[PDB]
Image: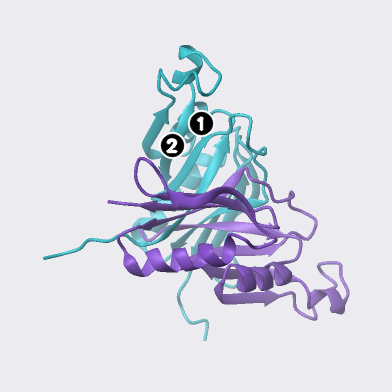
Chain colours: A purple, B cyan
Amino acid sequence: YMTALFPYIAFENSKEALAYYEEVFGATDVKRLEVGEEQASHFGMTKEEAQEATMHAEFEVLGVKVLCSDSFGRADKINNGISLLIDYDVNNKEDADKVEAFYEQIKDHSSIEIELPFADQFWGGKMGVFTDKYGVRWMLHGQDY
Amino acid sequence: GSHMFYMTALFPYIAFENSKEALAYYEEVFGATDVKRLEVGEEQASHFGMTKEEAQEATMHAEFEVLGVKVLCSDSFGRADKINNGISLLIDYDVNNKEDADKVEAFYEQIKDHSSIEIELPFADQFWGGKMGVFTDKYGVRWMLHGQDYTAIQ
């Protein structure tokens, strides 16, 4: 298989959410497709709110890709029914350290609700859980193979 | 003198009311394979507020594979929001990979008429290239099938 799974998140406003993931999660490789100036009327909006709208976006946190789009009033509010789990090899030093740097910047941040602090687990590995201000529940899992 | 290391990966982790019934459903409606289920142990049942019977029904952690991608899950217990379409699951594939395109085709062919599946966009060729379809299964998970075309439109 060359197939891959991406979560596809419906935000109230993706332009804003992408600025937030850039600033607080250190997201990189951000790509946004804004609603076009002449597609505005088709989505039922003014040229002005079309430039604040997103048809499709993607970003990368910790080397993994997340997809998103504006809700446009069609999608349910983001909850914790489906969480985003980022799994890494504790023995891949280069990713083990991106993860520690990432959690360090994240743990105390005002918009972040720590559910389980990122720490070594009795049976092996590291696990941490937290929910961002959009309501996305993130799970950090470090495994030793 | 080697070192095998694993690559960082994103997984969805789904909170089902019952993972056991859910995993049977994915097995038989979605052709899910590689199913691994960690139940609640007999002597863990005390901690979760349930008896021997309920614990063998319960799931601490599960995983399964659809079209070669891994989905993880467990039971909500009292703790998780109901599954909605705030976060959908997109399965991306190359339309010019014959092996993969056939599996995706066949999967969709066995799924579209099933009475648990609510089709939102029939799986179809898109104007600007590639394929795309969207549907919601019986547990409220919204799935997206996305076939990409790597040809320069030019």
Q: Which chain does the numbered disc 2 sit on?
A: B
Which residue has dot 2 on it? B62
- Residue drawn at x 70%, y 57% as measured from the top left: A134
Residue type highlighted by circle 1: Ser
Circle 2 sits in a helix, a strand or a loop, which is it?
strand
Give the quarter of the image for residue A123.
Answer: top left
Which residue has dot 1 on it? B19
| Disc 1 and disc 2 in contact, CB within 8 angstroms | yes
Q: Is there one chain holding both mark 1 and mark 2? A: yes
Residue A91, horizontal then vertical, whole percent: 30, 60
- Residue drawn at x 47%, y 39% as measured from the top left: B30
- Residue drawn at x 37%, y 64% as measured from the top left: B97
Determine whether, in the image, residue A132 is placed left or right of residue B47: right
User: Is the N terminus of chain B in the top left, top right, bottom left or bottom right quadrant?
Assistant: bottom left
Report how far apart the C-alphas of labels 1 and 2 lie in the structure: 7 Å
Q: Which chain does the numbered disc 1 sit on?
A: B
Disc 1 crowd, CA 10 A, few/some/many (<14, 14-19, 20+): many
Residue A26, horizontal then vertical, whole percent: 56, 72
Give the quarter of the image for residue B61.
Answer: top left
Numbered label tally = 2
Circle 1 sits in a helix, a strand or a loop, which is it?
helix
Residue extending farthest bottom: B154
Residue extending farthest left: B1
Query: Would residue A86 be seen by someone viewing this image from the given angle?
Result: yes
Determine whether, in the image, residue A47 is placed left or right of residue A55: right
